[PDB]
Length: 328
DNA sequence: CGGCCTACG
DNA sequence: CGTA
DNA sequence: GCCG
Ligand SMILES: Nc1nc2c([nH]c(=O)n2[C@H]2C[C@H](O)[C@@H](COP(=O)(O)OP(=O)(O)OP(=O)(O)O)O2)c(=O)[nH]1
Ligand SMILES: [Ca+2]
Ligand SMILES: [Ca+2]
Ligand SMILES: [Cl-]
Ligand code: NA
Image (cartoon, rainbow, N blue to C red; front, side):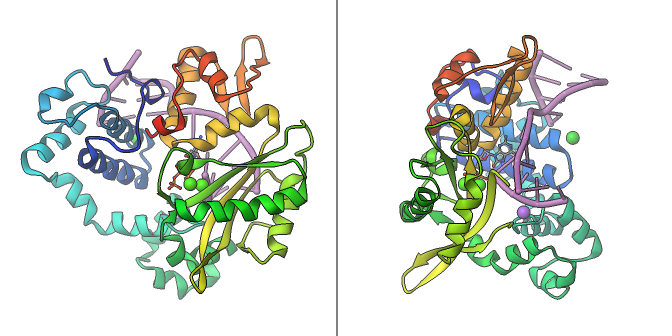
């Protein structure tokens, strides 16, 4: 009854198994810190199965038949149902390794590999990193300076005002260019850790060279606290107004030609697990290669022309899911 | 057992 | 290596 | 860790 791929079932933003999904996601995250991407995926997939269920899981027998629930994930759920707490999950939560890798990897510019190396060197706190700043990249220095603000959620209420300053710069850079809100906010989220915008122009080719022009105008307006600088993705830190002040916010800007816009919209709208599952489904079940630029048939060596996300789901033989049901 | 998404900066 |  |  429950299909094995998350892109085959609707997954709403809020659901009926929040506590169980959150515990499995802790185990997924810990697997990621240890470099076990397979274990990370299984725990994330099991969590997403629960998000897709129509009612709360009451008893272990309701997990029989569900995909991605074997010995380990089933024992986690069983302990939460019987005791309200999973010993394994709480042990991870209070471990020094978990807490430190979580704190380090949440820094912009620090990935699992860097956080792991710092952990092995004996570092444990942000103040530890600030005392040896010559070891840091410029990106990591910015992530560390702005860490407090960047750890505060961006509110959907902030986004409209930010979209209009981006739209102003985009319109000067290229009249007729459009800005589309993507990411979690497009899936209905009321907060997020960053804002994601997709930029295009209805005349194919006109978008070439656009993003540098946009970033030069935003920087001239004094709005850019950090950015990396030809390119098509920019990961920047923006000055967002607040009452009598301002706060730093992460903003991602992406440019796509209009021919690729449906693929880019699909990819940047997520969720991350949804898109990994969709790409896995495309390749393993349909023999087609999917990315944020297009959908390739490697037999005929042809790209599928899409005018909408609906087109892409149809070409993969999948029932259409609106963004709000892509919260795997 | 192999596989686990696929890009760009 | 980082980022999405 | 789980699926096929
Ligand atoms: N294919 C692919 N897409 C990814 C990856 N990471 C990642 O964030 N994306 C896509 C799907 C995400 O929904 C989208 C935006 O990323 P994000 O980290 O801002 O996620 P979000 O908006 O859903 O989350 P948030 O800001 O509310 O916390 O980018 C990845 O590793 N692979
Ligand atoms: Ca986001
Ligand atoms: Ca983002
Ligand atoms: Cl693994
Ligand atoms: Na990071």
